[PDB]
Length: 244
Image (cartoon, rainbow, N blue to C red; front, top):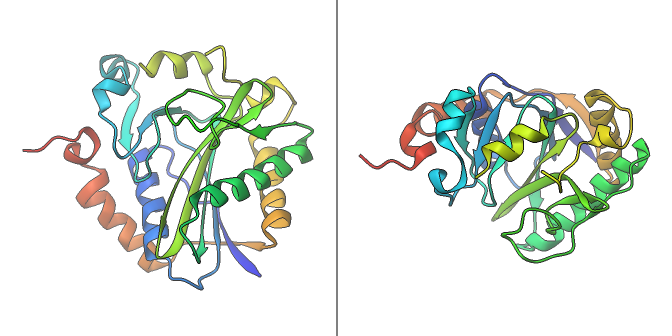
């Protein structure tokens, strides 16, 4: 089976990057080719859909440090991204609403990918959605979280997306989110972000049985993305939850 590998990123605009994920997920039709997207953001805090920003992040210190606030479409908690974090998202056809198995399946593909790099990791084991590390959506190199993920599901389609800490600033990450339990892939093995990407293309290909081939977004996906940015992701009402 053939998939679309999208190397699509706007690191200088996190809000547009998130628009892209929502656009690709929302224009997907059951039966389409599965999509693996790789991207980075520059200094950004991304809060979950249901989160109150001021409760989750130090907004004053974000301004001061030129950190972008963005709200994403999925749930889950707040995360700091910079160019040392590799993001990737998967949108595929879905026959069920089994979100637990989606995470488990994607986590397996991650674990297999990291093995290629010589890094031993496992999905966390705890069901407690509010803890910093060791959740079933986290990937743990032993005691250290090296990756988090969130997901959404609807009739016909499912979205999973992750941020892996490759060479992120772990001190800013802790300061922004209002440290001892996170680590970088490079804390373990000497790899570049491109070697990590390549390991993940291979691990997801082998694990999911998909031949991912480089592709670009369609005009329909683009246009939806631009529309979502224009009407939603670029606004303060969306990002900060302001009413009017």
